[PDB]
Amino acid sequence: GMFTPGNGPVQISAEAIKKRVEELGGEIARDYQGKTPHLICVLNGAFIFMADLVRAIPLPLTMDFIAISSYLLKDLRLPIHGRDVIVVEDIVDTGLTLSYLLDYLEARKPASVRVAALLSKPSRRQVEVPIHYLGFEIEDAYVYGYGLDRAQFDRNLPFITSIRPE
Amino acid sequence: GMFTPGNGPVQISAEAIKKRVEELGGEIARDYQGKTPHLICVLNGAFIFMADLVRAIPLPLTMDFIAISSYLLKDLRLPIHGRDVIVVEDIVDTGLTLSYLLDYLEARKPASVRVAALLSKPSRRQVEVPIHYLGFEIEDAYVYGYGLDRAQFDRNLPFITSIRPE
Ligand SMILES: Nc1nc2c(ncn2[C@@H]2O[C@H](COP(=O)(O)O)[C@@H](O)[C@H]2O)c(=O)[nH]1
Ligand SMILES: Nc1nc2c(ncn2[C@@H]2O[C@H](COP(=O)(O)O)[C@@H](O)[C@H]2O)c(=O)[nH]1
């Protein structure tokens, strides 16, 4: 029993991920100095990114967890009105899901909204959505690991890997 | 801006936590060899423990996330009937919540159910519940950090700390 990488074109080590997440955390801490952000994790794929990210943000903050599908499974529990909100996503593909979520959150009138996403495949972008804190921009490929699944499996791989289009 | 420990009687470093979680992961991997566990994370407090734990279990597995309160906020999404289920909890206090959850899960007839909890305060136990994979047994105190909150705050501290009864 060992963690094995797929043969896809995208591969990112736990160490590389670790270093990038720490930089993003430091960036957020700096940008939100003097404030109390409310980080909203988009389940299920972003829960590991969320876990590592928050531990790299030396600020007083709160968090929530929600589920959403393309075209809202889990609702918000804490108020976001007037809060400085930070959405934590796993990967931005077409951008549809994030687009719906941002409109949903904006309807409640938060003080501000910024987005943190571990990955982004801009060649697949169909709706322009903002990503203020991006881990890595990658080519078009189906990735998995580090929270992201492959038919519900492989969310436990400590690294990001992928399969071939075939 | 820096992570600061409270003055309570319970203090556990990120390093100590890291080492213990890795041992538990190795234990699960060994016990569940040849099987495909389904880990159910009890939100919100156990999401960091969950993130680190799964990355220390070199086995094919699936996961889900649910919310529950003393005396069921977020429901199950994946089937558990016939599955070898592992509940991932943050801390066992009176044991009431875990007791309800186990009965809930058992009603669906899983193949087996085992429990992993980062912490346990047995002096506060009112209902005997099983913990097959325990991180640390601690004295009675209100802890926070590493996913656990203090009025919704401090879930981001990379270590477990606590406050004084006063
Ligand atoms: N596991 C995995 N999920 C993906 C990938 N690309 C997109 N997704 C899923 O699709 C969701 C939204 O994609 P989008 O709405 O931007 O098209 C993401 O949050 C993610 O859960 C991928 O390459 N691997
Ligand atoms: N943050 C924090 N939460 C606790 C503590 N003790 C109990 N809880 C919360 O209460 C829930 C269940 O407690 P129980 O049902 O065993 O009495 C736990 O899952 C946890 O969320 C504590 O010391 N600190």
Image (spheres, coloured by chain):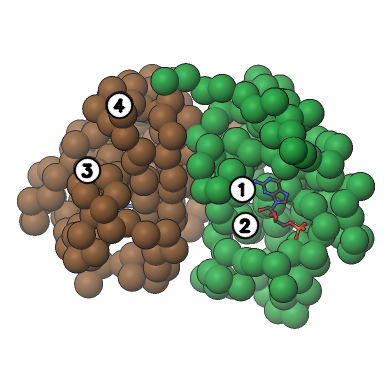
Chain colours: A brown, B green
**Which residue is under mark 4?**
A33
Do the residues bearing badges 2 and 4 touch, measured as CB atoms within 8 Å? no
Question: For residue B122, which numbered disc appears in the image?
Answer: none
Do the residues bearing badges 2 and 1 touch, measured as CB atoms within 8 Å? yes
Inspect this view and state whether residue B35 appears.
yes
For the residues beneath circles 1 and 3, the answer to whether they share a chain is no
Do the residues bearing badges 1 and 4 touch, measured as CB atoms within 8 Å? no
Secondary structure at badge 3 equals strand
Do the residues bearing badges 3 and 2 touch, measured as CB atoms within 8 Å? no
Q: Quick one: label 4, few (<14), some, or many (20+) residues within 10 Å?
A: some
**Which residue is under mark 3?**
A114
Secondary structure at badge 1 equals loop
> Would you identify the image quadrant in which residue B113 lies?
bottom right
Secondary structure at badge 4 equals loop
User: Between marks 3 and 2, how big is the CA–CA gap?
Assistant: 27 Å
**Disc 2: residue Cβ within 8 A of ligand 2's nearest atom:** yes
Do the residues bearing badges 1 and 3 touch, measured as CB atoms within 8 Å? no
Type of amino acid under label 3: Arg
Type of amino acid under label 1: Ala
User: Between marks 2 and 4, how big is the CA–CA gap?
Assistant: 31 Å
User: Between marks 2 and 1, how big is the CA–CA gap?
Assistant: 6 Å
Q: Residue at x 83, y 57 (%)?
A: B94
